[PDB]
Image (cartoon, rainbow, N blue to C red):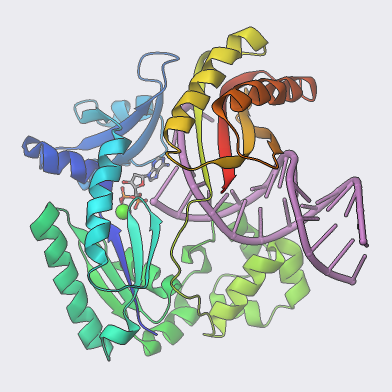
Length: 341
DNA sequence: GAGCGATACCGTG
DNA sequence: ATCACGGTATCGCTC
Ligand SMILES: [Ca+2]
């Protein structure tokens, strides 16, 4: 099959740049402000102008201001991005009925039955970059190859505003040459677990014995890596249906006082129930990030759907259970709803 | 031996 | 020192 992946460049920033074009050329950093102290929080994304200097998603806002104190610092407007994203997405549906929306920012199309070869495919990805630039003034990167993983690796290798095909010969090349840590799904913890085992390239997972590999990363990621290195990975493009929806909020100050967490918790329920629309969940999970930045949950499933009032009273019970069964103070509290009708 | 909710870990956005 | 999603490993229960 032939897979075409679209990955919007610097999406949150670029949307801010489309809306306020005075911003082009300047470093923009979309932030998520927390409210413990002035400029506490983290970076959600920056544009290339800011990324050049080490201002990337995940760093604290204070560090980003130490590097680029004169950049534009914008509060995250996710609702807006989500709305633009939706419209870019309804636009990708013109090019294939088989479409898998992977994130706010990313979609895969199986165009197998709308092109014959990768030159036709390549051609369809210029069209699509054009259409999106025309309608929404947003640059994207396209990656084309014979499955989702190598279509995503192609986009990585081509961004920003790129397009690249990874034909069957280049796939065999990468399986040998490409550092396994750049394979989607291999993050730092498992990258290291591999290097530990000498695994540096994908091909390497075929000489190692399966249960040494399984015993180290998981049967599933083991099988995942092996199927790639055998060039036998095919995962169909499948439509995403959201499974959970939650919200966590950081408290002005740590605590384990029940009457002190309760308003943040209840704020988190309100927000999440609004984010649910007509989705009725049967499961609720309360979520506390410890003072130590660990994450510890407590949940309950129900024969029925969960009303907000059920949500309010069950969540307090679940938070009580978090505080008994642990001694660590709470930095942020939230909830996740799931198992929808 | 292996199928099921709770819960943690791990990846990416 | 953000928030969000969602896949998989592990346990204990259960057949
Ligand atoms: Ca992107």
